């Protein structure tokens, strides 16, 4: 195996500037280096073949260069649809080896999240469990902090967080915070609040309810 | 022009599984056929390849003994067979076509990919719960409704709102494992002049257990 | 875009091998289709710079052949070989130069 | 000299 | 006998450029002229020394001919695409061989005018030099076309006239190279196999022309073994090479003989190390 190191692992650029991805190999592969793009849900799509051959139909903004051990993949004036994952693959000798990839995300303006809190549905209380859910929709950047508070006191155990991928149209993220308890331990307390710390606000966004 | 793979599979540890890859839109023997694995995090590893012309096979040493590649020329279909399956084999498996004629080894066309899950958990239908507001704290012009799909196996689960009529402000949160079963959430945002004046319904489909469930918010 | 003939490789030299005496190393690649092929001559596993190629032509059965050649000074410790890539093979074949074959 | 197709194509 | 042959190849490369076109001229087994559309400028270039004696108008006429044939082959590739219902994204090849073998006297022994598509036989002029032989239905369309147009008459006119005269001229001019005969230098090498048997290897180097016969007679004669024998390969300097190997038990080396039969030898060589 000839190892293949791709850099950087992630990148944040807006719409219209240069994106440069470096790919190094452990042996000499001549120019047999290929560049693939993969959008969420889809299989990867070949962008540049061996040498620096731009595949038919590929826009002219994408380019490749380098030879031997060092290779570069350049996007000039990136469009909004250019933001996906990018992989380099050498095709000099077997086994064929891929890079670690590059998560290219759209660096857009900051956006405050929309926060909502939901109590356990009655059917779930009849079942035997309880789930307090907190939605945090349409915000940028992806960094955010959720603080659960039960009756004023902070709760740390039993919390599961799920982020989404950057939206294709808004370029914003969303996040779901689920607090799981049993019906008994949910019944003992009444106040339930959800606190969100983000860059767009110096003071956190609080959304609460009273079980009654 | 087209590479159609078989549907998602769930198998027990130590078992075997056979995935198919039906090619169409080109002469099948004129191109090699590779298989590539993509894992949750550490992604993209070449498994091996076969020549439908003469059955010539190449394998990655990492997966030697685990993968059996065959190809049938009559139906123009490639097959990959995994054996002695562990948990570290759960991933997406692609059949990819190698460029023809020229002396090169890069791939040009990729199949849709087949998701393989190796787990001793039994297929479980989901539990669907609605998520309505705090009953009083409504104020803004928009309100957000939720659908919680807890306790199912395996993946994935499809969720639509009002039968796909409302696609604005809907977010499908990625499922997460919890107590060996999956949990998913879905959000939708509609104008406060719509709910609760107009009924809102989330439809959850789990194909692995052949279950569909409609839940009406409040 | 039809049949596939796997290339056949022969590595040799013109004059008998004599240590220190420069010579020509030949890679003779015959009986392959399609005509698109890639031939590299390696010394100690490293690619040799100036590699010259005879003009590609075919034989009676339409199978293409070609002859690559380079200058080389054989010693007793240097290793020479020829690597070939072709659409009919799963992986690039390497044939090492044998001073007796 | 060599042969000429004489523009007589297949 | 002697031969003047021309080997022509047109290969398509969609998405890259126009089809690559090459012509290679051979007298007997030696290349002497070449054309290639992928050069600094496409022209008919010499490949041997004796052919450079030709004047500039020779190369001019040959370059004109090669470019005309290249346009013909471009059109031919496109019509073959239409003929076989094939996609315009694949790479396809079209080969053409044309030439004449004449006897030591000068009478035409055999004429060749054959085509191939994707390494498979397409259409070939028969030995009568009047009728064609086609492989598949597209080739039958081509044959009926060429029979209406009467291309066999023109092709036979080339094969019986121009080809023979130019072969005679080439032999006359390159006498010093083409009609030379170089004796093979031969020797026997020995190798110890990992078992008790040993590999005997009979070489033949530096002979011209390539017509040679290497055989291994045992204690008496006959082959009676899976003797290894590689094809006559070119050393790259005008001479050729061949060898034949055999396995033999440890001790019988003095009981095995190699026979080298070459036209440049007064008496065939008998050998044993």
Image (cartoon, coloured by chain):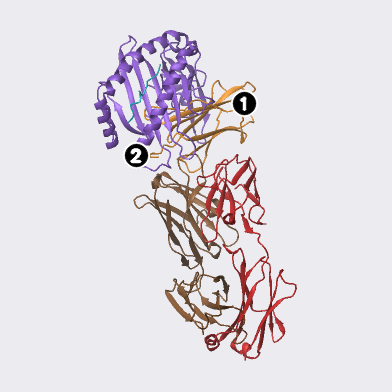
Chain colours: A red, B brown, C orange, D cyan, E purple
Q: Examine the rendered structure and indicate whether residue A198 appears above or below residue B104.
A: below
* Mark seen at residue C74: 1
Please identify the residue farthest to the right as the structure is shown: A202
Mark pair 1, 2: CA separation? 53 Å
Tell whether B165 sits left or right of C71. left
Let me know if residue E1 appears in the view. no
Regarding mark 2 in the picture, which secondary structure is present there? helix
E153 or C69: nearer the eye?
Answer: E153
Regarding mark 1 in the picture, which secondary structure is present there? loop
Tell whether E121 sits left or right of C14. left
Q: Nearer the viewer, mark 1 or mark 2?
A: 2
Q: Examine the rendered structure and indicate whether residue B29 appears above or below residue B43.
A: above
Residues at circles 1 and 2 in contact by the CB criterion of under 8 Å: no
Query: Residue, x 39% and y 50% (percent of image)?
Result: B25
Residue C77 point in image, percent of width and height: 64, 31
Residue E20 point in image, percent of width and height: 46, 31
Q: Quadrant of residue E64?
A: top left
Q: Examine the rendered structure and indicate whether residue A61 appears above or below residue A141.
A: above
Residue B193 point in image, percent of width and height: 54, 80
* Mark seen at residue E82: 2
Q: Examine the rendered structure and indicate whether residue C12 appears above or below residue E80.
A: above
Q: Residues within 10 Å of mark 2 (few under 14, many from 20)?
A: few
| Chain for numbered disc 1 | C
Let me know if residue B216 appears in the view. yes
Residue A171 point in image, percent of width and height: 61, 63
Q: How many marks?
A: 2
Tell whether B167 sits left or right of A19. left
E261 or E255: nearer the eye?
Answer: E261
The quadrant in which the N terminus of chain E is found is top left
C6 or B111: nearer the eye?
Answer: B111
């Amino acid at each position: 195996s000839t190892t293949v190191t791709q850099s950087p692992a992630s990148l944040s650029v807006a719409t219209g500037e240069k994106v440069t991805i470096r790919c190094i190999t452990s042996t000499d592969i001549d120019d047999n280096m290929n560049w693939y793009q993969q959008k969420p849900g889809e299989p990867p799509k070949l962008l540049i073949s061996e040498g620096n051959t731009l595949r038919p139909g590929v826009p002219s903004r994408f380019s490749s260069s380098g030879f031997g051990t060092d290779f570069v993949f350049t996007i000039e004036n990136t469009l909004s649809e250019d933001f996906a994952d990018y992989y380099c693959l050498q095709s000099d000798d077997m086994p064929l080896t891929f890079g670690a990839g590059t998560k290219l995300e759209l660096k857009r303006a900051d956006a405050a999240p929309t926060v909502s809190i939901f109590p356990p549905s009655s059917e779930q209380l009849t079942s035997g469990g309880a789930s307090v859910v907190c939605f945090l929709n349409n915000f940028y950047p992806k960094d955010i902090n959720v603080k659960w508070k039960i009756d004023g006191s902070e709760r740390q155990n039993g919390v599961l967080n799920s982020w989404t991928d950057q939206d294709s149209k808004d370029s914003t993220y969303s996040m779901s915070s689920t607090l799981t308890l049993t019906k008994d331990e949910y019944e003992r307390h009444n106040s339930y609040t959800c606190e969100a710390t983000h860059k767009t606000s110096t003071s956190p966004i609080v959304k609460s309810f009273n079980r009654n | 022009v087209q590479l159609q793979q078989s549907g998602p599979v769930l198998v027990k540890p130590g078992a075997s599984v056979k995935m198919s890859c039906k090619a169409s839109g080109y002469t099948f023997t004129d191109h090699y056929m590779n298989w590539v694995k993509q894992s949750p995090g550490k992604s993209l590893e070449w498994i091996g390849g076969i020549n439908p012309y003469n059955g010539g096979i190449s394998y990655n040493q990492k997966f030697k003994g685990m993968a059996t590649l065959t190809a049938d020329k009559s139906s123009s279909t490639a097959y990959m067979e995994l054996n002695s399956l562990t948990s570290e084999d759960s991933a997406v498996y692609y059949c990819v076509r190698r460029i023809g004629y020229y002396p090169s080894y890069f791939f040009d066309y990729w199949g849709q990919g087949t998701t393989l899950t190796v787990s001793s958990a039994k297929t479980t239908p989901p539990s669907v719960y609605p998520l309505a507001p705090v009953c009083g704290d409504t104020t803004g012009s928009s309100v957000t409704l939720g659908c919680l799909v807890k306790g199912y196996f395996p993946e994935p689960v499809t969720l639509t709102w009002n039968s796909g009529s409302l696609s604005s402000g809907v977010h499908t949160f990625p499922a997460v494992l919890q107590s060996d079963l999956y949990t998913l959430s879905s959000s939708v945002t509609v104008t406060s002049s719509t709910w609760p004046s107009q009924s809102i319904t989330c439809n959850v489909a789990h194909p692995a257990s052949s279950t569909k469930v409609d839940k009406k918010i409040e | 875009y039809a049949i596939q003939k796997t290339p056949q490789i022969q590595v040799y030299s013109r004059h008998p091998p004599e240590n220190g005496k420069p010579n020509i190393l030949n890679c003779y690649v015959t009986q392959f289709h399609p005509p698109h092929i890639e031939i590299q001559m390696l010394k100690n596993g490293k690619k040799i710079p100036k590699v010259e190629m005879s003009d590609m032509s075919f034989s009676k059965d339409w199978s293409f052949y070609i002859l690559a050649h380079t200058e080389f000074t054989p010693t007793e410790t240097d290793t020479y070989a020829c690597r070939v890539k072709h659409a009919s093979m799963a992986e690039p074949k390497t044939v090492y130069w044998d001073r007796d074959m | 000299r060599g042969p000429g197709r004489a523009f007589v194509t297949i | 006998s002697h031969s003047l042959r021309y080997f022509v190849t047109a290969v398509s490369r969609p998405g890259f450029g126009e089809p690559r076109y090459m012509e290679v001229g051979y007298v007997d087994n030696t290349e002497f002229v070449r054309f290639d559309s992928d050069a600094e400028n496409p022209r008919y270039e010499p490949r041997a020394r004796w052919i450079e004696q030709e004047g500039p108008e020779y190369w001019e006429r040959e370059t004109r001919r090669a470019k005309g044939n290249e346009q013909s082959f471009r059109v031919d590739l496109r019509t073959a695409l239409r003929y076989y219902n094939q996609s315009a994204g694949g790479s396809h090849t079209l080969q053409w061989m044309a030439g004449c073998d004449v006897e030591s006297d000068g009478r035409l022994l055999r004429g060749y005018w054959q085509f191939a598509y994707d390494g498979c036989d397409y259409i070939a002029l028969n030995e009568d030099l009047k009728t064609w032989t086609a492989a598949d239905m597209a080739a039958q369309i081509t044959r009926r076309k060429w029979e209406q147009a009467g291309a066999a008459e023109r092709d036979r006119a080339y094969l019986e006239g121009e080809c023979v005269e130019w072969l005679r001229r080439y032999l006359k001019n390159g006498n010093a190279t083409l009609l030379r005969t170089d004796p093979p230098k031969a020797h026997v090498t020995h190798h110890r196999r990992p078992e008790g048997d040993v590999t005997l290897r009979c070489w033949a180097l530096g002979f011209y022309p390539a017509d040679i016969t290497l055989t291994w007679q045992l204690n008496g004669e006959e082959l009676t073994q899976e003797m290894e024998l590689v094809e006559t390969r070119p050393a790259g300097d005008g001479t050729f090479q061949k060898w034949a190997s055999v396995v033999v038990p440890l001790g019988k080396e003095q009981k095995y003989t190699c026979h080298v039969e070459h036209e440049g030898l007064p008496e065939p060589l008998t050998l044993r190390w």
